[PDB]
Image (cartoon, coloured by chain):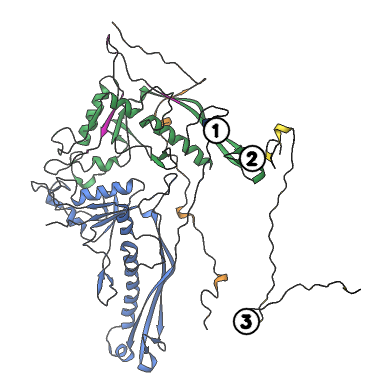
Chain colours: A orange, B blue, C green, D yellow
């Protein structure tokens, strides 16, 4: 007879740690990188010169 | 993940999708390692030296070596430690770099290989430590061109520089022996399997449940020896430790596989 | 969940703009890689030990020269660790190219040949409940771009709505004690890629690709 | 509730409203206090029952 870990089990709490717990990281880059145009409607037209004499 | 969605009231593309997030669990489990050092009371009396102070130094050092060998290479690792050893993490991730015999015309001399291993860890982590065997300064010096000029620093004049910092990685040197399971020796670091390891230090946790304690025994039965009946004594040493590796940072909808560890392997050819 | 909803939209926008991954059919512009590839502004890295310009630094200079012809290159786009790849470039004798000697060798990532570096990472919808990468390393080592020729239209920036009575995905929220966050944003993209060169309609790109060494 | 679907009733579409009530509870009985070497059986409760005869 010896009062093993399974006889004492109800006295033995596991602990918890946040050391490896993180949110998602914001990896997106195109809005930070390229110039942004604020659109007032679904479609916008951009005229460009195509040819010259 | 987001989806590109349309503007219909009834068609399937006019409704927004649902999605989950998921968490998982990793465990530190404390495991015990120990030794008992028995000796005869007459030998303690007749010796010039304090043999109990010497055996007290031997017991503590023996445990620290066995911990290092378990974490780095998985040598006699407890079955309850769910994490991969550092070498096993890199090896399963395929983050393994072989040193070559090219005089650095390949990227594959040891200094080039350290940068390739650093790049592999830097892909999803911050590498910060280089683990190996000592004398690295003498191997960083003496790296040579196909012409025999030095690769590492300008000229041989002042060439064995500091070990302590190498390619922005802090160096750490491992040495000694551990139980081979057959009453011989195995090395803490096997130089035939790895030249060095690159690691992100922050992804390793060493749990210390009980730091090394010494007990003097003068009446116990140990190893089948009845100590007091044989006019003997012993020192008992034990500590309790755990290890976890933060290896698989999430990447998306599927469960990811990564390593914060890369291994550099010696030149195996002729 | 608020962080996850926001981040998930940003990743999907990057993958559409760079490589055309799940790009909306109404976006008439080529994606960055597709613009350069169709313009033939593609520089393959080689293994000459830089006896040619075909090492990665010589390849970056060639790709920048292709853009600098009609446009003004400003950014280098790629995956991270570029410092470790610019270090460890070697002569036919094995000496380093990019800096004098190996001793101090992993330099700064942040500025390469006068181009600002931008690093891309993460995953997006594969169209089958799996993952696809934002940057496809099998087709590009890096992209050189004139930043001024890309316009990103923000019609509605990312918005969050809290739902506590709705039906979503067949789940009646209120009778089940569930809640949901709804995330959406509205975006557009255009590339100013064919500046006029004469009396015939031109074919240029403000984008050039460096592609990995495929051989041996 | 005023917009939800509850019990098949689309509330807004039918000019209905509802009140939703919930609470969360648990119970434990501290019986079987230990008496010795063997796991003991004993209740903190005794019941009085009515006279059955006629």
Chain letter of disc 1 in the image: B
- Main structural element of the magenta stretch: helix, strand or loop? loop
Mark 3 lies on residue: D38
Mark 1 lies on residue: B15
Q: Magenta residues? A: C188-216
SS assignment at label 1: loop
SS assignment at label 3: loop
Looking at the rendered structure, whether the residues under marks 2 and 1 are on a common chain is answered as no
Looking at the rendered structure, whether the residues under marks 1 and 3 are on a common chain is answered as no
Measured in 3D between alpha carbons, the distance from the residue under mark 2 to the one under mark 3, in whole angstroms, is 53 Å
Q: Residue at x 69, y 72 (%)?
A: D31
Q: Residue at x 68, y 76 (%)?
A: D33
Left or right of B169, for residue B214: right
- Counting from the top left corner in percent of width and height, residue B80 is at 42, 66
Mark 2 lies on residue: C164
Placement of D44 over or under C145, stated as above or below: below
Measured in 3D between alpha carbons, the distance from the residue under mark 2 to the one under mark 1, in whole angstroms, is 18 Å
Left or right of B173, for residue B221: right
Q: What is the quadrant of residue C195 in the picture?
A: top left
Count residues near mark 2 (Cα–Cα under 10 Å), then give few for <14, some for 14-19, many for 20+.
some
Q: What is the quadrant of residue C14 in the picture?
A: top left
């Amino acid at each position: 007879a010896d009062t093993n870990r399974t006889d004492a089990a109800a006295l033995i709490q596991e602990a918890y740690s946040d050391v490896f717990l993180d949110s998602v990281s914001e990896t997106a880059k195109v809005i930070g990188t390229f110039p942004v145009y604020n659109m007032g409607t679904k479609t916008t037209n951009l005229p460009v010169l195509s040819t010259f004499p | 993940h987001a989806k590109w969605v349309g503007e219909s009231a009834t068609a399937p593309e006019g409704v927004k999708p649902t999605a989950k997030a998921t968490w998982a669990n990793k465990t530190l489990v404390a495991e015990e390692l120990a030794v008992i050092l028995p000796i005869h009371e007459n030998v303690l009396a007749d010796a010039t030296e304090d043999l109990l102070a010497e055996l007290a130094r031997m017991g503590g050092a023996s445990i620290g070596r066995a911990l290092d060998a378990a974490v780095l290479f998985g040598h006699q690792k407890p079955v309850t430690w769910a994490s991969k050893s550092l070498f096993e993490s890199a090896d399963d991730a395929g983050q393994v770099v072989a040193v070559g015999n090219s005089n650095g015309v390949e990227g594959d001399d040891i200094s080039g290989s350290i940068l390739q291993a650093a790049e592999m860890v830097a892909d999803v982590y911050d590498p910060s430590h280089l683990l190996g065997y000592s004398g690295l300064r003498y191997r960083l010096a003496n790296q040579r061109d196909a012409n025999g000029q030095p690769l590492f620093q300008p000229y041989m004049q002042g060439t064995p520089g500091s070990d302590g910092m190498v390619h922005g990685l802090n160096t750490v040197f491992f040495s000694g022996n551990v139980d081979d399971g057959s009453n011989g020796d195995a090395p803490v670091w096997d130089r035939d399997v790895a030249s060095a390891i690159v690691v992100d230090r922050s992804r390793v946790v060493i749990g210390v449940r009980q730091d090394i304690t010494v007990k003097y025994l003068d009446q116990a039965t140990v190893g089948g020896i009845n100590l007091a009946e044989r006019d003997m004594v012993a020192l008992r040493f034990c500590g309790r430790f755990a290890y976890a590796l933060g290896d698989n940072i999430a990447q998306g909808r599927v469960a990811a596989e990564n390593s914060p560890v890369a291994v550099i392997t010696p030149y195996a050819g002729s």
